[PDB]
Amino acid sequence: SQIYQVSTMTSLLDGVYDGDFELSEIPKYGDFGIGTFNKLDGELIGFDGEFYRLRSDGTATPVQNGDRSPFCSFTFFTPDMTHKIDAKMTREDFEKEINSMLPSRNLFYAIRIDGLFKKVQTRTVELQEKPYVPMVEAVKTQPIFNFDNVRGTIVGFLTPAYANGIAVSGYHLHFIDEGRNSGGHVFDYVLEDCTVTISQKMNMNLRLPNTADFFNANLDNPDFAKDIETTEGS
Amino acid sequence: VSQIYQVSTMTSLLDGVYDGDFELSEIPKYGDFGIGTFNKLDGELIGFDGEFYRLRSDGTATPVQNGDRSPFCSFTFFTPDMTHKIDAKMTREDFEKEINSMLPSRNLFYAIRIDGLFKKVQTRTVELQEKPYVPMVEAVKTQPIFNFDNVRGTIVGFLTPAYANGIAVSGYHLHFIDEGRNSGGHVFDYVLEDCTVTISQKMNMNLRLPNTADFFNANLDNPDFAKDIETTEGS
Ligand SMILES: [Zn+2]
Ligand SMILES: [Zn+2]
Image 1: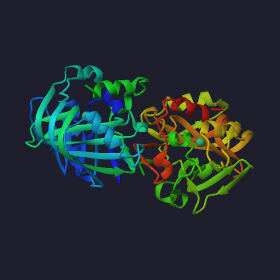
Image 2: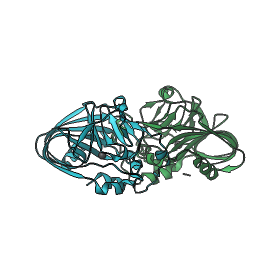
Image 3: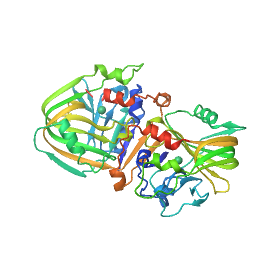
Image 4: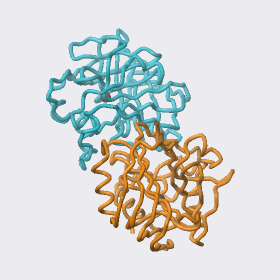
C-alpha cells in the first residue's frame, strides 16, 4: 500500500501555491488525507472518504469536483493497529508513546485519533493574492484557533526523516470537530480520551505537478528543514 | 511508464544495510533501464533496453538472473523524450552543466543515457562485504577503481532533484558498461570523445521500502548524510 504524495513541501515553501491536482481524483488515490488548496485557501482533511476545506472564517466545506491543490497526501486507510488513550495525555507524551510502538521509524504511517480533546490548537492558512510570498511570510498572519473539551478527529501522517522536504518529517496532523465546522492544521493538543488507529505503508508515490510554476520553482533552500519547523509549528 | 521505481534509500545503504529483499526477477515489472547495487554490495547494477548486468571488481559483467537480490536500485521504462549530440571532446563538468541547462526543470526526475566513445571513464565497483557489515563510508575505502581510455560503451543513470537527496543521490548518478560487456562500474569522472545523449523525463517517483528487519531497525537519522553521500559517490 502507498502514501500518494502530491508535490513537495519545499515547493510550498517557495510560494508555489497553485497546483494542478484536482480533488475530483481523490477517490482514485485514497479515502484519508491532509493538505491544502490552491492559493492556500484553507486546510484539507479527510477520512472515511469524506474530505473538507477548513477556512479561517470557522467553516468546513465538503470538497468538490474542480477544487485544486499544490500539496496534499492521501492513502487508503487500513486499521492495522489500534490503541486506547484512557485519560489526560499531552501531545509530547502521546507522540512519544506512539513512536515507541511503531514497528519502525523508517516507514510511513497514517494515524487517526477519534475522541475528546481537552485542548486543540490549530491554524488555518488563508487565501493568498498574487504575487505570492514565501510560506514563512505567508503564515505570519494566519488565524490560530484554540478549542477546549471538544469532540472530533485528529488525522494525519508520520513521515520518516529521509522524506523531510518532500513531506513533513515526524507527525503532521490536522483536526476537525464532530460538528464538521472547525479545526485546521494542528500545533498542539491534549487528549482527554481517544481511540488511536494506525495504518502502515511500505510505499510513497510522489507525483509532481505539470505546472510552469513548479517547473520554474527554486527548490534549493539549504535551510528548508528549519523553515518547515517554522511554518508547521506554533 | 511515468515513474522512477526506487528500491529503498541511500541513507539505509550508508548505515550498512546491504541486504534487501528486492528480487531482480521482478525488474521487468518496473523498468527496462536502471542502476544500483546487489545484496552484500556484491557488484554494480546497470541495465538498459531490458538487459541488466552485475559488474564486479574482477573485471567481469554477468547478466542478472532470477534470485539476485538488491538493497538499493532505481528503474524506469525509458522513453526517448530528448536527444542531443556531443560532437567533440567534452569534460564531465562541461557536459553536466550543458545538459543541466537544457532540462525543462531541475525539479523533475530524468533518466539519461550516453552512447558512444569516451576518451576517459573512471569507475569503481563496490565489492562483496562480510557480516557484520560496516557503514558505507568505511566499506568504499578499499573499492577497486578502474580507468578506461578511448573506450566504446554506454553511460547510464539518473538525474535526481535535491529534495530527494538521501532517498536517491541528488544530481547525476551514472554507471558505465563497455560495448564488450565486461567492464565498467559506478562513474566518478569521464571525458566524452563523441556520443549520442538520450533523456527521459519522469513526473513520479515511487519509493518501495523493503520488508526486512534490517531496514526496519536501521538508524536513518544521520544529520551528516549529504556529505556522506558526497564521500561515497566522489572519487
Ligand atoms: Zn498541514
Ligand atoms: Zn552507483
